[PDB]
Every structure is written in C-alpha cells, then in structure tokens.
Length: 227
Ligand SMILES: *C/C=C(C)/C=C/C=C(C)/C=C/C1=C(C)CCCC1(C)C
Image 1 (cartoon, rainbow, N blue to C red):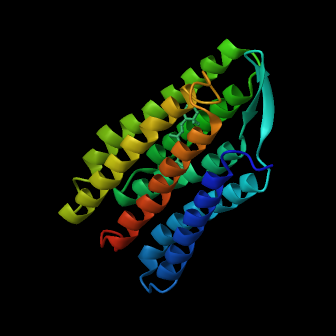
Image 2: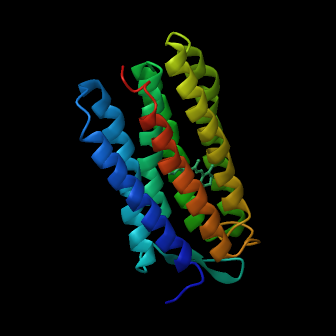
C-alpha cells in the first residue's frame, strides 16, 4: 500500500528484532538461575513487539473506524502488543523490589483495564465517547505510575544501593515514556487527528523501542539482576 508510515514500521521491526536477539543470546549464556526470570521476561518484550510490528508492516493490525465524518485508520495491532508487553515490563520492576503478590496482581489488572478501555475507545464510532474511554484508560495508567513511584520506590529501599539505584532509573524511564502515550493518542489519529498518521507512528516507535529495548539494556546490563 506504500502508506506514508511503513518506514517507521520497518524500523521498529528492525530495532525490536535486534534487541530481541541480543537479549536472547545474552540471557541463554547466563548460568545464574535467579537471573533467568529477568532475561526471559525482558527478551519476551522485544519479541512480541517485533511480531506485531512485522504484521502491521505487512498490512495487518489495521482497521478503518468511522467518526468525525471521516473513515479513520486505526492500527489496533498496537493493543495486541501492549496487552502483553506492558504488564511484563511491570513484572520486571515488581521482581526487582521484592514486590508483594497482591501488588503485582493489582498492577497487572489496572494495566489490563488501561489497554482494554484503550482499544475500545480507539474503536468507538461516537467521537466524543472515544475520549470517554481514553479518559478511563489514562486514569488506570496514573494508578500504575502512582504505585511505581510511591510504593515500589519505597520497597527498593530494603535492597542494596545497587538494586535501589537500578530501579530508580527504570522507574524514571518508565514514568517519562508511559506518560507520553496518552498525549500521543489524544492529538493523533485515535483522537483529534491533529498529528498525521505518519508522524504518530514515528512517535510510537521511539517510545515503544525506548521503553522496551532501552529498558531491557539498562536492566540486563546492571548487576542488580543477580538476586
Ligand atoms: C512497550 C510498550 C509500552 C511500555 C507501552 C506503554 C503504553 C502506555 C502507557 C499506553 C497508554 C494509553 C493511555 C494512557 C490512554 C490511551 C490509549 C493508550 C493505550 C495509548
């Protein structure tokens, strides 16, 4: 179809694929059992992002939704990606600060709501309602971020300065990147359609890749993954 954004899809596929292979080889060569968890989870993020990025590049994960008097292109494959990749990244942090089971449960659930109402809004035909679902999805994200900032950061204090310092970095990267998605959605094709689809795809690959490959490298290169 030669759509104005295939350039960004092919670059995301390439970066996600590269990060996936490096983590895979870096994780399968480690003998520390207690380290496997982090490597398997971290390699699994790029992995999923790769496949979904490849599908969109090939013309899938796309559907036209009617609203605003137009037939808007909605790349739904993104949510199929985020549904499994966000809670997995949340788990990496949870296993890092000795996060309690009840906490992990609440974070995974809130995350489920976030992507759930997120896709529903992106598929809604009543323009104004799309922003209703967007509003609920965003609130769920702020909850997760609250727990990550106030809660998780407090537990990372019972760790060594090595585990507490690696978490603050991953927490900071997660807070900055996750915070930008709702805005990108709001002013993009799923929202006010102010920023064209090609730019939007560019903004997402940068965020996706930074929050996945950029997240994995920091976590896997550190020595705080050695329980
Ligand atoms: C690898 C992907 C990552 C780390 C994705 C993070 C995605 C978010 C924090 C997405 C948030 C959204 C909202 C707050 C509301 C509107 C719809 C979403 C799903 C784009």
